[PDB]
Image 1: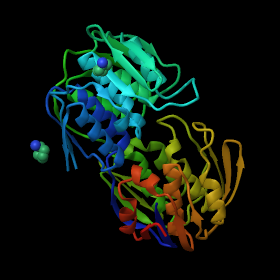
Image 2 (image 1 turned 30 degrees about the horizontal axis):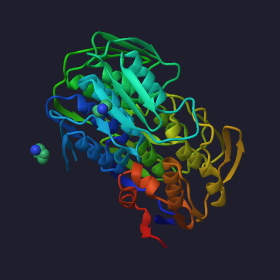
Image 3 (image 1 turned 30 degrees about the vertical axis):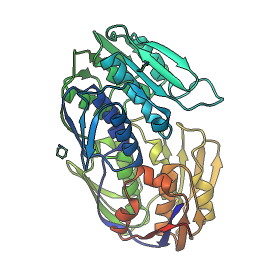
Length: 419
Ligand SMILES: [NH3+]C1CCCCC1
Ligand SMILES: [NH3+]C1CCCCC1
């Protein structure tokens, strides 16, 4: 059980190169199962889920190799069943189902059990494929799908916004007969990236990024080269790292237009920001940030995945700020940990009232959410003394070696194996 020992306070300044988004690389890697010709997917991060995905694709008959790119040859996929042993640690494995049924007419994926029913993650994927004409078979532990001929385009109205089901329906629809229209489609940049990857292969999709996506099915998809977009949450995390430490940073290989809400909030906190084609710079000019008011909402609004980071920013800012979370009902576990580090905050339902303090104090802390855990590491960078963040494997699964990037910005951080 690795931990990070962080010693502060340190001002974080320098340059950081943003990694590709795991949340775009994953749907793209599964969409590659539709490709009849070789594909090179560039800017893919080296994270556990990518390894799990490559192993799963290999089990299906895909030829896969990687470095910064992942090379895929799905010309000879010949096993349409994703087994429990390879999918048990990754819910994203459901994304193998739609491409297999759309291209080969059959697919099966193992699913984890549970006593709870109703609004389970996989449900909308199942009903989406059923609307496209697939026959679905369910038994506890798995979902099997098949189609007699080709899937058929359909007009689908999503009752609730779902990134996962939008990807499943959009990807499978590329090989359906006719036109598919997805109403109330998820608008996330990762949806746009996946749609653009499919178009690079020969698909016909429009409306990605808006609440209505239209797909005109084609007979087959080819191959090509595609570069995964930058991780917007990693970008925001490093921008906040500079903003809370009186720092100055340049994030390279960034995509500013995926962070409009975040950049606006950082400007309200007092940051001097400039943006280029593929970069963002932030300079606090040695100043403490000013408190801000934040309400999370679906993209393109302020992202819930930046909420913990901005809570930390408010907790060391000048003034009182309120953070309101409207996406998740219990995403404030970072707060008690920051209170133990000296922060002043009150939890009122789905809001946290923050009263900024000048300095935090080191403590032994831990959070299970990836973003909350990364925020504790950042707090450790600016807190007086030593902070030990436990169970950092959560961070390791979503950030490509964060301690090395932070160390290059001036952080005093060490990975400790055990104690
Ligand atoms: N054959 C491909 C995989 C290794 C790198 C060059 C292309
Ligand atoms: N008997 C089969 C069910 C669908 C995937 C391939 C195996």
